[PDB]
Amino acid sequence: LVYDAEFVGSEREFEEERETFLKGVKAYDGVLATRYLMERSSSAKNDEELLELHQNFILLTGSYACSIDPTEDRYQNVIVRGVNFDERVQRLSTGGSPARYAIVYRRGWRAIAKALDIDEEDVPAIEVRAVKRNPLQPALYRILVRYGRVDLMPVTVDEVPPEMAGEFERLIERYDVPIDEKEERILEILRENPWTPHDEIARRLGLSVSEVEGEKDPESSGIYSLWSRVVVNIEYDERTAKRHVKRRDRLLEELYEHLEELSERYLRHPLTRRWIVEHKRDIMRRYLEQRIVECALKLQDRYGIREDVALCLARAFDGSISMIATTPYRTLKDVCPDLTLEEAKSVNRTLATLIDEHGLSPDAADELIEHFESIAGILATDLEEIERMYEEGRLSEEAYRAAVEIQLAELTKKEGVGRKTAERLLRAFGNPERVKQLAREFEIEKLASVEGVGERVLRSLVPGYASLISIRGIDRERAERLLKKYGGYSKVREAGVEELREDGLTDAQIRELKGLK
Ligand SMILES: [Mg+2]
Image 1 (tube, rainbow, N blue to C red):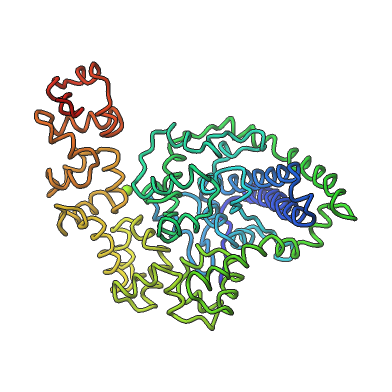
Image 2 (cartoon, rainbow, N blue to C red):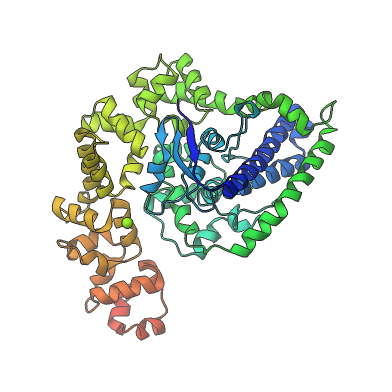
């Protein structure tokens, strides 16, 4: 399977990138070693000092990762398990760095280390996927990395805000971000336990992981998309970024000296970097071991997969069910030759949907899985982009038509939207997710500017709009202004009488609004 990329900036920019990656490797090494130490004894395991050290390594790995490709243009032809990542990120509305996009995937460092000439023998791993012991809300942590948020990644555990962890919804509320109905289902689970694994959330909501996760772009649906919506609204703080970068190298050194000192409790020979290098492969295996077992068990018990295949797929994707669920049938078969199509459809539900619902050959479904990852990845892509790929010759007729039908149905599903209106909405606004974003933000006039989008379509698409506009003498202009002012319908309805009067409502209208009389 191909992992590759090339360096495309200046010599200066090259030396910078190299230094950063190696500092990130150094930090990831501390993640692995402390985890190794935590499993080495059981007094170790309940050692709060040891857990904080392990969390400080996670933050510093996070921080260094955030610093990759600061100009978003230093890397090209980023390929990860055969997938072109340049194309993947450029099709998202916010674009961004394809190298950091890569890093947020298991094994994504292999591509990036190659661009930078770091010997495979060094095993220069960086991973930023920690869930259970992550000091940050995990989806957020990955989103900070994706977006290169050196300003936002805390550089010490004592410095993590509660709004980035146990009180993470404060951050969402702070930037007034609209949340879809699916996302509110997600949030009910997350409020209770911010560190709930994504596959557990999916299980409880009866959804796939890709449905829960969404694309790492504002114009999607699910936790990644929600966080991306928050993060791109937080203006970059250059000074804080500089302070973090300025502190972090010394912090890393102190972590190592703490590591060595702490380890004199649970080992016989001290734990140095030299011991890391020597034992690197073993500690990488110890790190993954429980993930792999858990994934295998699930694939067998939850998706009916044969026991030998279950285990073969777990090891191949480092225990990540979410990844297996978004890998082309041909990539799955590549790494695990005994796998059947039926088993592949069982765990890859985009695959099963495309084949069963849309009449695609495994091969034509794989085109879409390769290019878009999932049904959610298709919904997040501009129709014109998909069309262009089919013009270019890079997407079969059959794959293109299913994509269009998938996009149209996300709209025709709503009362009053026919195929043509739906096609017009996609030409005007890009994709179905962007249409729903505009509706969540009450952009009634903008939405009504497209031919075919009268009162009916608005009533189905815009939440609260139907409720407000049925109050007599409130008009489309005022509904929009009201919905934007208070933040939605419940909030217009609970407004104070006096402030509603200054909005121009009569007492008869407020009375009716409030359900009085
Ligand atoms: Mg757009």
